[PDB]
Length: 150
Ligand SMILES: [Ca+2]
Image 1: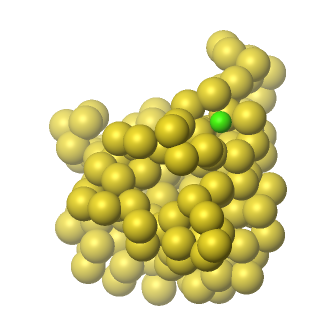
Image 2 (image 1 turned 180 degrees about the horizontal axis):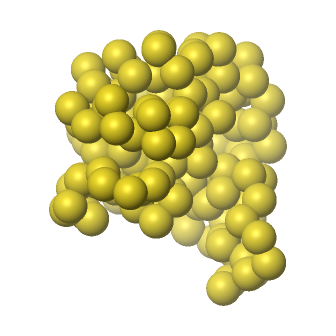
């Protein structure tokens, strides 16, 4: 229920993908500016310094763009990763040994990566990490870093 992110009608994949981009881009204008990402990129997904994602994605600067992410994602390792790949990925990165249940519940992959990187609500089909914050933290950190860097 917001124009910015999460619109009420039906959660489309674009609003979702821009939402996880919006994790960095506070105002969600389609591109994150350096100031917008200040704590956000660094910690919220890079868990240290966002120089990696900023200078890897843009290269010359620090601006990340939703549609550009869309194009990047389709060209990145993430969009190529099938369920098996994502399963080993989710475990080795997200540290969620609930993989059996979750993959059999929703069948995740490179599409699911951005779709699950936003809120527990989306990803928890039935039973998947009781801890909301711990769930969304692990998933957003690794899924988002995966859709962004890969
Ligand atoms: Ca912005």
